[PDB]
Amino acid sequence: TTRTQLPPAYTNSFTRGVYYPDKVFRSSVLHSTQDLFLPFFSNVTWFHVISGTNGTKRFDNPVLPFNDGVYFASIEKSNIIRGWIFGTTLDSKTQSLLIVNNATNVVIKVCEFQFCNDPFLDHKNNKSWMESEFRVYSSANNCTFEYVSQPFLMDLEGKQGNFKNLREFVFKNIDGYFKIYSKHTPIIVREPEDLPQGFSALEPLVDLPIGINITRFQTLLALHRSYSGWTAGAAAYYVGYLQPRTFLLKYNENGTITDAV
Amino acid sequence: NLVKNKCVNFNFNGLKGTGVLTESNKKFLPFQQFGRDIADTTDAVRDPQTLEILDITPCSFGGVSVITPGTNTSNQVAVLYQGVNCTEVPVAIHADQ
Amino acid sequence: ILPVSMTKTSVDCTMYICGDSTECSNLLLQYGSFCTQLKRALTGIAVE
Amino acid sequence: DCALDPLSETKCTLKSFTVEKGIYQTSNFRVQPTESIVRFPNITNLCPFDEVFNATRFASVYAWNRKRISNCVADYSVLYNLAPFFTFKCYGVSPTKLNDLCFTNVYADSFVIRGDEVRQIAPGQTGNIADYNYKLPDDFTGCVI
Amino acid sequence: FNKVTLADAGFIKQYGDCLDLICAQKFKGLTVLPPLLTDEMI
Ligand SMILES: *[C@@H]1O[C@H](CO)[C@@H](O[C@@H]2O[C@H](CO)[C@@H](O)[C@H](O)[C@H]2NC(C)=O)[C@H](O)[C@H]1NC(C)=O
């Protein structure tokens, strides 16, 4: 629709954005490494996606520059945030990524597509036919890489309310590799303003050997219908850029990062 | 990938080293593969076949010393093996030592 | 309080530098006796 | 000598024929390895790559089928052993140890061949069917199968 | 002795109980020789 622009806000990242550098297990040792890391207490945007103007779609999905990595996270309650499409020019002439969560399959694809002006998804499954969610693209020319496996998210919600997800993700591409780190934990208070102060370690999940040149970042939304236009619930996500740093890491007896400096 | 109680060379993930592979009590995380110590040396490894990890300790090695009264007055000598269990190095180890 | 003695230590060059490498032992052999001075000094230190 | 007896090694280290009373360090001892623990990544999979090679139909020369071998451990020595598979020689890589050496992004093609143009599908010459339908780059990769 | 013992040579020189700072460095050619006079003779 004819929605208006929204000036992005800022929030302090606190002591978050630390991951396991290597697969090697080390315990009770204070190892120091040189790698890209999120600086402690840095500004991070706190984009919040909610029902805009009581029924007006909000296109708060900018083409954020990928640069050297991201610290995508969320305080998501129900399943509304999906898609981490990437693109140099975001057209049919550019190889692009698309990380869907179709049922229980990631369906990782590396093919050229044409992207709608405001692509989106339906959180509720379409009746009868499979789903009209493939509206994001209409043409697929050439295909390089395909990957189908278990869904990248193992978060459950059907249990009960009063607790939401705290999905955290780091997207890093270097020397023809693509690594994804994830970690989930429950939440105590519904405070959407700032990130709670707690240490979290981002374990590697999937590694890809593709060599796509990535420069921009795009996010998709899951809205079914007015349940005017396309509307959904409340959600919030953060973007944290990654820059080189030097850290001193302290391991525990079990080999899990407890704190770092 | 399996043998126990004998320090042997291996090619675990390209690593070529010799040590006494034995049972381990470390609780590796599901993704973790290799083990290290304070001196930054391999200490434990992930089992390829199973999910029970093993410890690597190099087998016994050390230096020898010779105690002699002086070649004058007898040539009898005694041999001291520094810092090793006597049971681990009896007089019958000459087959593999 | 006055210090009196310290720890007696011994270092094996061949194993420390080239741990389990016969080719390394043959190559180190061309240097002569580069380890007798260290061993003698350490033994003297221990005796001292 | 310097290996007959402890007195011999003591004399060898002292570089003298006479030894006084005392304790001397001569050499070290190390337990040698006994066997090999064989080593295996314990991979449990075999590539389903025979579907493209053998199927109901073969792709035409003017329209090759698009299929690639990825995340596979497909053995090529069984192909070398197979009598029908007579071409296993490799111009730029190992003919018989091609499978053992690691590689990535292997692409497959299907094209009908008369039989006498196999020598001409390679770069540098034009075959009866390779003049207009099939081709290879200036320095073709892979091996002829 | 209780005040000084936060770190010492380990008191261990049999090497049998090593399965971790000294014996692990033992695999790197750093050994400790025992004193001639024990602490009960001193
Ligand atoms: C990891 O730290 C725990 C500390 O809790 C160590 O002890 C474990 O404690 C939990 C919770 O009390 C028990 O459920 C486990 O059975 C304990 N493990 C035991 C007794 O072996 C644990 O040993 C540490 N693990 C490592 C590898 O250091």
Image (cartoon, rainbow, N blue to C red):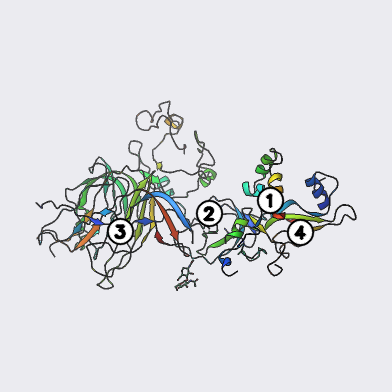
Residue depth check, mark 2 versus mark 4: number of the one nearer the observer = 4
The quarter holding residue E27 reads bottom right
Establish whether labels 2 and 4 are both on one chain. yes
Give the CA distance from mark 4 to mark 3.
60 Å
Tell which subunit mark 2 falls on: B
Q: What chain is tagged by disc 1?
A: C
Q: Residue A14 shows which numbered tag?
A: 3
Q: Residue at x 46, y 30 (%)?
A: D119
Left or right: B79 as drawn, with respect to A230: right
Where the N terminus of chain E falls, by quadrant?
bottom right
Tell me which chain the residue with mark 4 is part of. Answer: B
Marks 3/1: CA–CA distance: 52 Å
Whether residue B31 is visible to the viewer of this picture, yes or no, is no
| Residue A165 image point, x, y percent | 28, 65
Q: Which-is-in-front pick, marks 3 and 1? A: 1
Closer to viewer: mark 4 or mark 1: 1
Q: Residue at x 12, y 63 (%)?
A: A226
Task: Please give the name of the residue rendered at 44% of the width and 29% of the height, measured from the top-left corner.
Answer: D120
- Cα gap from disc 2 to disc 1, whole angstroms: 26 Å
Q: Position of residue D53 (x, y in %)?
A: 42, 45
Figure quadrant of residue A58: bottom left
Q: Amino acid at mark 3?
A: Phe
Going by the numbered disc 4, the residue's amino acid type is: Leu
Residue pointed to by mark 4: B80
Which residue is the extreme one toward the front? C1
Rendered view: B4 above or below A245: below
Q: Which residue is mark 2?
A: B40
The secondary structure type at the circle numbered 1 is helix
The first of marks 2 and 4 along the sequence is 2
Amino acid type, residue under disc 1 in the picture: Leu
| Residue, disc 1 | C42
